[PDB]
Image: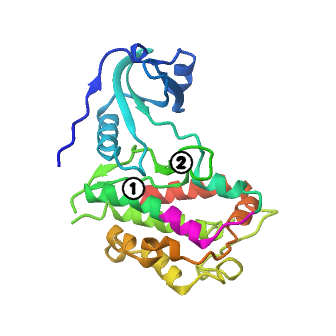
């Protein structure tokens, strides 16, 4: 089966979409902005990149991935002049529902089940499975890059931000770092904190002491050994021994999310207790990923 290649349009974007240029001001800094199609009136999102080799690759790899339903769609790409600089203006579907874990943390009943975690992990695994099956590694799978279509409870989770994405060759282990990311996200979904040692952070709990067993008791006591084994496989130190996306998506815990117990988890309640640490969680995931990609 044959798919079209990426046509980068050269006409000014404002022929096609309403923007106005105090909106564009905040854009070249990095913020995704809201814009409207003129013909259709549908809302979209706009990312502004400086045109270089690397931005070109990001947009290329992302375009190949767009038709995955667990990956944010590229609608159009423009090569325009903005300010003194040549820019890639990328038009995408708007994802208005916020980040994955924000939703979980803000729940009013502080209730979250193993089954829900499984359902979410299936969504993320589908996007990764698509990428790895066309020899792309994302290499920046992390909380801020997983976003919901809308605020509503049945919104679709989607993967964004191809700024670190890369073509691979199989004999390669570039894909390994995506599998580690899955293990980390899964771990947080099940307990509310990452599987990170720290030498930290007052008026707060230390969730995992250095060198301590990785599944501590208050939060992990009702979680099966089967699930802990799936996590050890995803987090395995050596990339040569780390679980692949094929093994992950073929695991019963993922394949049969419907049959997963509705075990009540500490996740939402822990995300709230520890919300002052969330910035540091993300910061540590970002640093780890940079040593691991």
Say whether residue 201 is visible. Answer: no
Drawn side of residue 220 relative to residue 9, left or right: right
Residue occupying the point 76% across, 69% down: 205
Q: Which residue is mark 1?
A: 127
Task: Reply yes or no: does residue 227 show up in magenta.
Answer: no
Distance of label 1 from label 2 (alpha carbons): 13 Å
Task: Reply yes or no: does residue 117 show up in magenta.
Answer: yes
Quarter location, residue 196: bottom right
Residue occupying the point 55% across, 48% down: 148
Q: Is residue 224 above or below residue 55?
A: below
Q: Earlier in the sequence, mark 1 or mark 2?
A: 1
Residue 170 or residue 258, whichever sits in front: 258
Drawn side of residue 172 relative to residue 248, left or right: left
Residue 222 or residue 202, whichever sits in front: 222
Residue occupying the point 43% across, 52% down: 70
Q: Which residue is mark 2?
A: 147
Q: Secondary structure at mark 1?
A: helix
State the predominant SS element of the stretch in magenta: helix
Residue 119 in the image, given as x and y percentages of width and height = 52, 65
Residue 142 or residue 152, whichever sits in front: 152
Quarter of the picture containing the C terminus is: bottom left
Q: Which residues are magenta?
A: 110-121
Q: For mark 2, does the 10 Å Cα neighbourhood hold few (<14), some (14 to 19), or many (20 or more) residues?
A: many
Residue 119 or residue 175, whichever sits in front: 119
């Amino acid at each position: 089966h044959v798919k079209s290649g990426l046509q980068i349009k050269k006409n000014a974007i404002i022929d096609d979409y309403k923007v106005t240029s105090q909106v564009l001001g905040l854009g070249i800094n990095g913020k995704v902005l809201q814009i409207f199609n003129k013909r259709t009136q549908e809302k979209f999102a706009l990312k502004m990149l400086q045109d270089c080799p690397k931005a070109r690759r990001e947009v290329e790899l992302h375009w190949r991935a767009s038709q995955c339903p667990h990956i944010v769609r590229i609608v159009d790409v423009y090569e325009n002049l903005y300010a003194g600089r040549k820019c890639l203006l990328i038009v995408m579907e708007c994802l208005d529902g916020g980040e994955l874990f924000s939703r979980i943390q803000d729940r009013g009943d502080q209730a979250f089940t193993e089954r829900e975690a499984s359902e979410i992990m299936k969504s993320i695994g589908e996007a990764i499975q698509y990428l790895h099956s066309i020899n792309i590694a994302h290499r920046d799978v992390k909380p801020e890059n997983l976003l919901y279509t809308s605020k509503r409870p049945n919104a679709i989770l989607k993967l964004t931000d191809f700024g670190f994405a890369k073509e691979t060759t199989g004999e390669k282990y570039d894909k390994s770092c995506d599998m580690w990311s899955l293990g980390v996200i899964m771990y947080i979904l099940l307990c509310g904190y990452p599987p990170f040692y720290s030498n930290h952070s007052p008026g707060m709990k230390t969730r995992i002491r250095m060198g301590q067993y990785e599944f501590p008791n208050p939060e992990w006591s009702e979680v099966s050994e089967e699930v802990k084994m799936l996590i050890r496989n995803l987090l395995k130190t050596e990339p040569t021994q780390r679980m692949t996306i094929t093994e992950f998506m073929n695991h019963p815990w993922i394949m049969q999310s419907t049959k997963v117990p509705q075990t009540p988890l500490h996740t939402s309640r822990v995300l709230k207790e520890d919300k002052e640490r969330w910035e540091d969680v993300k910061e540590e995931m970002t640093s780890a990923l940079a040593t691991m990609r």
